Amino acid sequence: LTGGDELRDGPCKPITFIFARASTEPGLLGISTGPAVCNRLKLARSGDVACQGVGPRYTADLPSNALPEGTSQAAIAEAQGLFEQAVSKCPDTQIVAGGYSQGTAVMNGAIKRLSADVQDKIKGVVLFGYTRNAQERGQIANFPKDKVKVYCAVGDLVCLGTLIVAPPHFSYLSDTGDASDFLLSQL
Image (cartoon, rainbow, N blue to C red; front, side, top):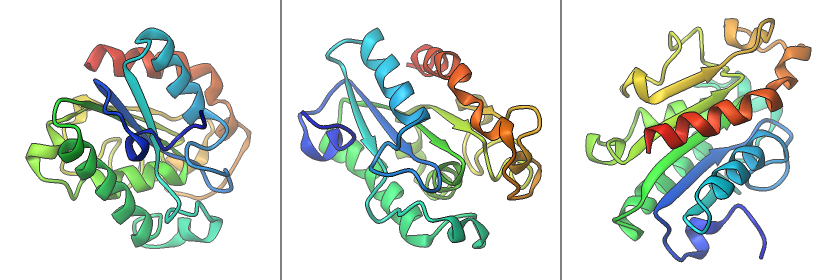
């Protein structure tokens, strides 16, 4: 009945969407792009999607953006554990994933650390306002470029190797349909 913990709650679904929210967002999926994409996936594949947010160890606090990899080690470990848990708990699931702002740093840090076998189960990843875009040359490290789509709005300065938050950083509602479409196409 409540959202964002559907991998931990079970039952397994054919599609598991794992999402890391932006700094300051409450809850597991957050309150912006994470639910927007989750809900689009559920409309397109009714009854086939589990949405799982990265939390609560990932606290989405502002200061963590300045740490080496752009988020906390705890957040990266939590996300990495959820990818591993999807594959072991639900061997038939196909994973799609995403993040927003700091959550994109969580995704990059976690996915780059996964084995090839678990990476192969992750069919697509959408990154809105990717805070590691410059640092990672527009992809996730140690993971295929063609499985990632980055949404960096014009003038969203966090994609330029800064932590400056400007208005285009909040313009991603208009990209959530494209993002859902990309994830569905990868599935």
